[PDB]
Length: 49
Length: 49
Length: 392
Length: 147
Image (tube, rainbow over all chains, first blue to last red; front, side, top):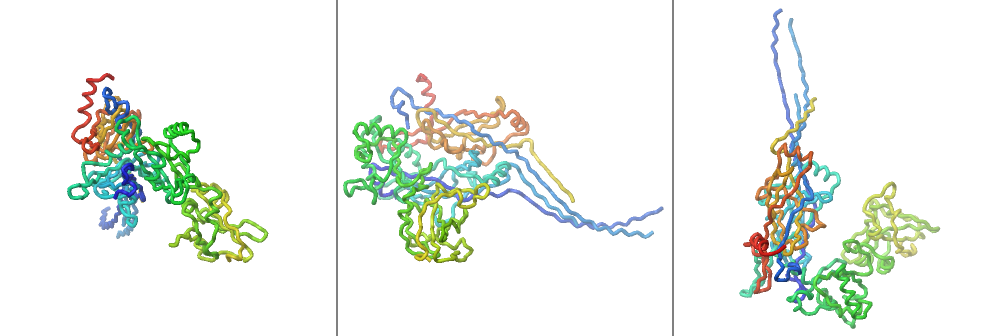
């Protein structure tokens, strides 16, 4: 895999690596919830006056 | 990489490393929560007197 | 009947991250088992996190001029900080409002780990030695060699290193003598077909030479002793030394801080824009040269009446990308893909057509203040002027 | 219709820390696989933590008169205490209140790990030996040499 111009003795054969970013995907860590409720009251009110 | 001052037998070649801090980032570990409720009541009061 | 709704948060872990990255090797020899160290920087120099690449993001082989993964494949994700890839990369609340406001986040490359594969004389194979990395070798190449950067192939910078002699190290004074002519003839592929140093077609005097502070000091000492003024005649007598930087660019264009070709001159824009292949309301399949076509922005048409005025159809900052590319070498400068899929407005065949273009030292990258959303403060060059009976 | 709001805390884990650091070699010989032990001091001599640098904060080469990372690059982050970098450096409520007022925080450098690279006489190459560090060599120099 050494490129053909580096097979002279006086030319150095060495890699040059660098990383480049293409997308940044940030995800908001946030928790959420809903709730329902159905109350049913039956009263028996007695009065004695 | 041994610098040319120390390519002499009578000069020692040794590293002097120290670390310096250029920023401090402190993050208050605190959790916040909000809540909204809606509620409707249908009371049908009856009395026999 | 009661309804509710809740939301929660935390002001130290309010977001996560995921970085799609790709590796490039623009060097001269392959690097095996690649693990780069890399850093996510918010704003100017506020670093969120430094991540050495984990096991999921290891590149087993990276040949020169290759990518990991391939160019047809989607990039790899970096979403871990733990050594076992169990912990995400988070943000507090102040680093999250600043990122949704300004949208500024870059990714540096501090270093690269990777191994070296050496020939086995026993069975003729090639075996990766996992005890030897490339970091023992690159600080020895960089101190005993001269460096030459040259951009005469597709206007991209190619860096090569050549073993030259250091006169203050007794092991280094054994290497053979390196002259500046011979260093070009073996690294990039120059020649001399008529006794003059040449690239593929270009004479060596079509380029210019820029050194660093230390190198240019040493070149002037070599030119005083040779009784020479022009460097282009004593190219076979300039001795190279260790730690020399030399930059060789094409003379015809303009260069920015990163030495990229980003602007041209007023004469070169009419040399490869002379002949026209076809002429109609829709077709500009032209022989635009590969030098200027990467440094221009787009094209601009101009309506010209009988008495003479300035009318522009594409008089807007974003209506200038009318550059389509076919598979025949002629870059298809279409006219109608920004015109509502309707043919262009031509009211009289006596009216001629004029087409122009802008480089990138006159192309702006943001909308202006009040009403300059158009070609007001954009200077161009006259390119096209023929009568409207040969185009139609 | 009801609006509610809730703000919690924990008074031994109130804040975290993320120190941006950078290494400097003002010496004479290069050091490989640099891993400094370093302590974050609050106030005069009250130490919150001591962190030997983990694998994210490892400098492969540090030549003389060099930096890691170089001056055109942003510094590296040090935000872990666990050996596998999965536990953040923290502080309690009294340390967090005093840090907002006086803003006195500094960074000592207690010691530095790092290997040596020797010439191999067979094939001329230079190979880092991962068995010996500079802490064997450096006390031998300070007892025989004049500074």
